[PDB]
Length: 315
Length: 55
Image 1 (cartoon, rainbow over the protein chains, first blue to last red):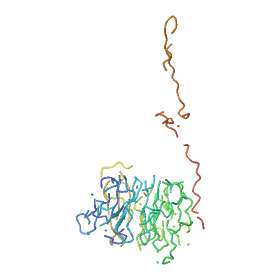
Image 2 (image 1 turned 45 degrees about the vertical axis):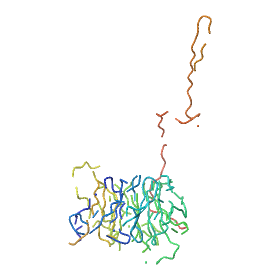
Image 3 (image 1 turned 90 degrees about the vertical axis):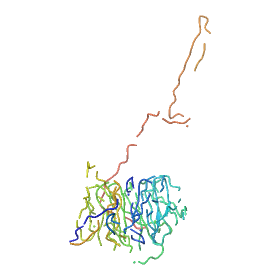
Image 4 (image 1 turned 120 degrees about the vertical axis):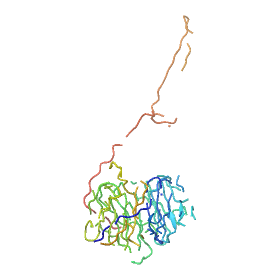
């Protein structure tokens, strides 16, 4: 039934959209990512023209943003980039509470646990490093031999003990899940055929996805740690997306979005629309995606310089 | 170098030009500006199926 219809975008950046972020406490309060050294804050007013007011740039690094994770409260935006950081931005404002420095090779990430505290970040030095909500390390993990690509938060409804769990990534072709308090050892994902360039997580504590340079999307549990639904999607995803509470997958496969539908096992609905003056090898192929925090609004993002948000509505 | 020889006859010049092994060196450079050198990647083994551990 669900005819998914393709609508007004929100265009704005000069470089190349490379993440994007579900606001995670004020789902308007969009908050978007970059390549050309900012973060254009887009409202969703919504009211039609502009779908819905590009109200704070935020400028820079010196170099290219690969991320922009919102807090558990959702008004404090956490940077990264190719000049070896963080720089915690204020969503409201233009400012740098705490330069977090220290890496060597080019952050690839950023994420924040359910209370806004013991943050993490991958790298190319081939680690990891915790930097609390101060430029300071708990510790500097080293179990991987590689470019560890991405790490995620998971959002726990066994109501949290308190010695918790997070995750990771990927040229050694593996994952590894680090107690976020005292980085202990828990399981990994063996097998794959090249680069793990992403992963994702459950919106309670028992779901995950990884993904593709091979084609296959190798799925989860964390609270079963057993390898799952093994799909086959040709090119790659660069750019994965849970609906929050539907059971819909969203990931941007080059080519679709393949909604795969992680219950039964079907292709509902592929969005490759809209398109004007190209030689293929121009599509202006994505690099970040999200599901309205409250879970409709897919904020579909693309290279080019035009975000193209595309919600699901009625038959 | 130029080492002035004061034969009888008439006078000379000598000129030597060593070249140094880029490796044997430490002085700055370890090559020419030309020399581009390459690894012969790695020898990997394919897939299996899925598979995971508990620690």
